[PDB]
Amino acid sequence: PFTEIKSGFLERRSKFLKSYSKGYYVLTPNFLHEFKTADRKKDLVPVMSLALSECTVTEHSRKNSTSSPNSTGSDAKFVLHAKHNWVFKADSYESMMSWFDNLKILTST
Image (cartoon, rainbow, N blue to C red; front, side, top):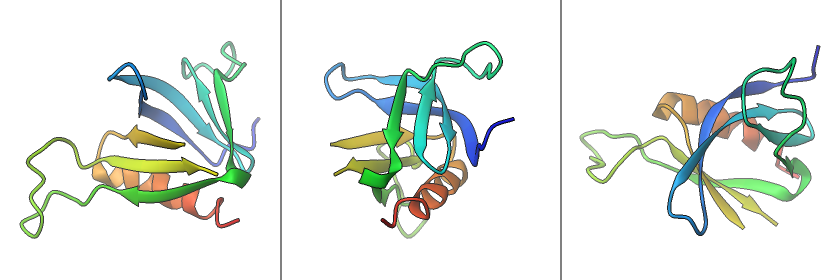
């Protein structure tokens, strides 16, 4: 058992290393926790826990459509700001939007 609201894999962009690192993320009413693996029985200490009380989600990609074709890269990104700005990338626009929305309602402050 666990008061998990949402969990799943995400890539977080490194600020210095110019690369993404994939982690397994678990959203609770209190934190977004990062774990190395999805094994909630054996992998039990977060590599990082972001307190939601002082985060906000600001922007997200615009879907790849005829109205705004996104030639550059993926359209599955969002920004989580700490009160600096972490860039996360999900599997798809749809998955990204589920993370964004679920984060939004836990961080209205």
